[PDB]
Length: 237
Length: 300
Image 1 (cartoon, rainbow over the protein chains, first blue to last red):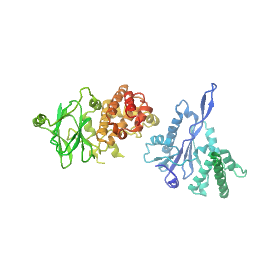
Image 2 (image 1 turned 90 degrees about the vertical axis):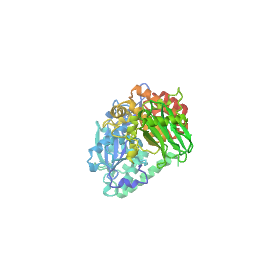
Image 3 (image 1 turned 45 degrees about the vertical axis):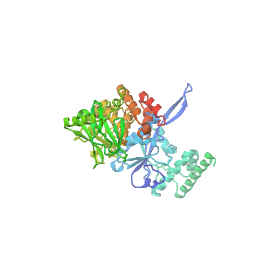
Image 4 (image 1 turned 180 degrees about the vertical axis):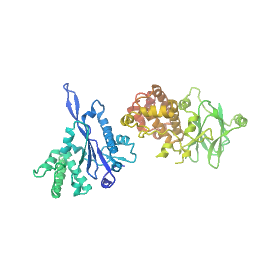
């Protein structure tokens, strides 16, 4: 059934699984028309499909042309997310196909289930976890490849960079969710924490800075403080 | 007007005939039901006074043979049997009528209720849902499971309703996932009407038979089937106008007949709210919407 705090270790076992987040598929700016009505203009989006064990990210870029002359776009966006995940699974060799797909939003269940009818042994699960994958587009290199796309494109990343060389997938996921939670709560302050020190760079082939083990502890502490500092403002507590 | 004689009533029982019912006392000199209207199916049904567990009954058509009821003290129920000897049967019925040992099917001349509930129900379709080809009449009870309930355990005792499943390859054409899921017209019109039922009359027969089994036996699988066949039409954008008009009439008489006190168990909130207020056909069921709003406003 639902993935929660109770069954959290299951994310790091040897059963292939993928998180699917559809938050950034259909993205708009709302603006005024010359007549003083309101209109939306779509921008490029992405499906965020992540193997939490390996860090492998299947970033499917959703080009604005998808939406041209379509109606009920927030509804279509769930079905298009499901079409593209189903197509990804069918493209993978059998031994690479997931056993489970966990959707971060319950509205993706029926669309994904219907598109995956050909795969009755792949479980489609919701989660009770509130994962911060919406903040994916706060990661500069992911944001850049999405906005520059001129056509539908699939880009493959490791969202853990080379972390699994030094830490477990449990710890790598904890680090990723803390970074994304911070970027989601206060993007400016999170980016300042990550790039404030000029001597620490991001490798051409990486998403995040090249931090030593001790620098990661400091960064992780600064991220926790940011999230509490911000929660201190929100609620005045 | 045909007759179903009873050998005797050795156990205290509530006897149903169609929408009517009578309490019979233990060893009361009851010998059956006369004046049963020719031209419809009928259902004769039972609920023992000493064990209300297992409502059970028999669907029959008096045109297909001479049928009687006899209590079996071994299996502990009223059984239907066919009398093949025409002259023995007529002779038995004539005797019981003379001694006025039979209740009269109590049909008011103005009242089309039974016709309206069974308009599309045919014995030959019942005998394919309820498989026991040695008998011309069909046994149903409270506890019998459907083929679909059994998939999700004795095949011989199943209700073989047509399986309907909105998240099945049968319901969803490869490459038309969103279209077929949001608009079930393909599934209704091509798969079910043209494909399996052949026509709207057979589809309505099964819908009406599922309802009556749900109402008279509290058969939960039957109730699921009735709701599924309503939802499949209401969730289709493209339905022939004659089918919508007929559905409105069918559902109106089902809601009209339903005991007021069973609406909590026999009506599915989600299906009715969706069908009347959100679906493609929300504005196509005027009679059904007015009786539901006036009789069961809490459900909605």
